[PDB]
Amino acid sequence: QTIQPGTGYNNGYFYSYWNDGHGGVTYTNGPGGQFSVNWSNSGNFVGGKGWQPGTKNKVINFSGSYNPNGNSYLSVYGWSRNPLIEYYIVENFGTATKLGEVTSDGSVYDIYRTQRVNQPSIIGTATFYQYWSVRRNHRSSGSVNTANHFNAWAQQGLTLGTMDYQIVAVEGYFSSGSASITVS
């Protein structure tokens, strides 16, 4: 069903849907691991379905339709605690510091680390690091072996702590678009 921001469990899956208070986002939970989102001149928002907690060895399957107009991400998305890390495995997008590369699931990824200062997080406003794996061959369906990325991040010294949630998420940032995604 169409819901307001928050977290919970739906049809066997953990979901998280967050936005910055701007209207113009419609997030809908569907059957199984399905979710859909429409956004028109939104602010910043994140929503998707997955697992609570995640694991460092999950192979995540996804397929769907992804049509952004502006800044947007379709990625595997999740959080760590001790250390507090917000991580991204970007499979597709709309319109730092490079630490290395990794070849996985039919494409090369570029490894980046960024820092967010005094920003919303799962523990509230905080300062934390972000890890990025960004696919060069964009796609909207396939499977991601998270262990390939986590071990690649660890090689470059990027540590992950206690795995929090782990979802396939659509992110928008002052843009418009539509997406419908099935996770398994």
Image (cartoon, rainbow, N blue to C red):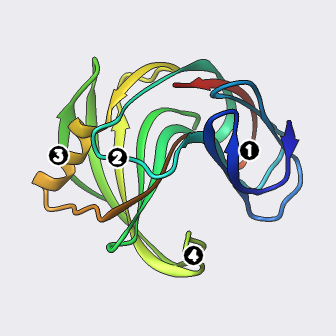
Residue 110, disc: none
Quadrant for the N terminus, please. top right
Which label sits in the foreground, 3 or 1? 3
Judge left or right: residue 64 versus residue 134: right
Q: Crowdedness of circle 4 by 10 Å Cα count: few (<14), some, many (20+)?
A: few
Mark 2 touching mark 3, by CB under 8 A? no
* Amino acid on which the number 4 mark rests in the picture: Gln
- Cα separation, mark 4 vs mark 3, equals 27 Å
Residue 175, disc: 1
Q: In the rendered view, would you say 86 is above or below 138?
A: below
Judge left or right: residue 7 versus residue 61: right
Residue 55, disc: 2
Q: Crowdedness of circle 3 by 10 Å Cα count: few (<14), some, many (20+)?
A: some
Q: Nearer the viewer, residue 154 or 34?
A: 34
* Amino acid on which the number 3 mark rests in the picture: Asn
- Cα separation, mark 2 vs mark 4, equals 25 Å
Q: In the rendered view, would you say 88 is above or below 158?
A: above
The local secondary structure at tag 4 comes to strand
Which label sits in the foreground, 2 or 3? 2
Is residue 57 shown to the viewer in this render? yes
